[PDB]
Length: 197
Length: 212
Ligand SMILES: [Cl-]
Ligand SMILES: [Cl-]
Ligand SMILES: [Fe+3]
Ligand SMILES: [Mg+2]
Image 1 (spheres, rainbow over the protein chains, first blue to last red):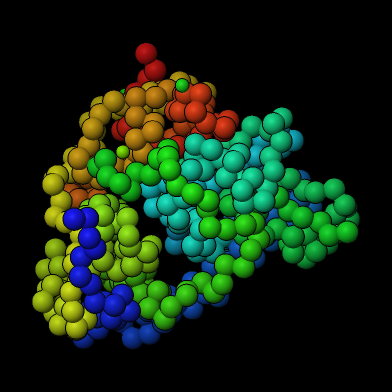
Image 2: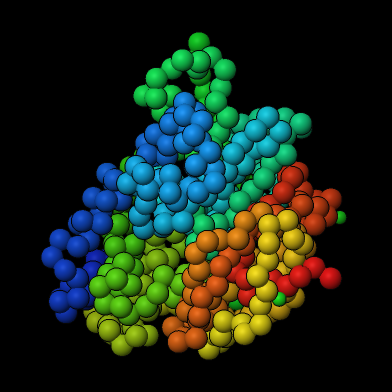
């Protein structure tokens, strides 16, 4: 009762799916290898970090990013699959934003990178919408009681990025310096950018 | 579909398996893991055989215990394989022959889907809306925690998309609708049993109605 079904090893199943389609001429030459390269090298949270650093140092761009995220991202050429309609959400001294896909995994791939395993976990998908404060605490991020937490559930085609607050101690940093502290988890919203001593 | 995939609000899970900024390792942790997404895109863009919506739904159609014990990328191997069989592109026999063993698929759909609603309302930022108190056995992009609940519009998209409940079943009558960022107070969704502030759900126009 309740037992798993018999299954061939997953690698064998996945490659069987490839070979069945490839052997019918349905998969162009180099196709999956091209996607692998896009997913590994192009889709990256370094892009979202570039956008945050620009916003932090350019009020005009900040305004654009917050009002028409698609247009702002397009300036950099970073629209793409799973990242065609972008909304950036602003953290403030009284608001912390956090993103999830409770139904599956949806993520702004081109600017955040493909989601990490933990983001797709049942634990995150079930819990962050109901107890985000405790989830973030457990993960290492304490959000004070004076701060409303707002969870965006990625249920349609909007693809989100968080614009975190800029920490003290970074005044006058270059865009490159600022980018370094905007991590993937800052863009998802579970982390706050950290400044070293 | 009120499946086990509709996890938001479920209680009893443990810690999220991450601490902030920890090493997540490479993008792909096994040499096959780029295949499900790549082959999904082959199906959508190259073959024209199915939509991304149909992929979301076929994963929802995994047998529930099977869903719960299957790693993420494997669910999409299963789902894309299933669609290829259902669409007549591949056979389960050839998949199992190539795999050298069993390759169970998602279960058949129990709904033909439904059309884009004929009667909907264009909402404005600041307006109060209720999520329609409806039950859809097939695909729907409405997590049950918001069914029947009231919130306020934060955004109306400037683009429109096919209605999931139709295109997720390969129907011809998905039309197009904008979606709305609907902000709900945490207490509206979970009463006293929440530690959050607000939750914003991105809801197709056809899931919404004016609040009373
Ligand atoms: Cl209560
Ligand atoms: Cl209506
Ligand atoms: Fe998702
Ligand atoms: Mg349910």
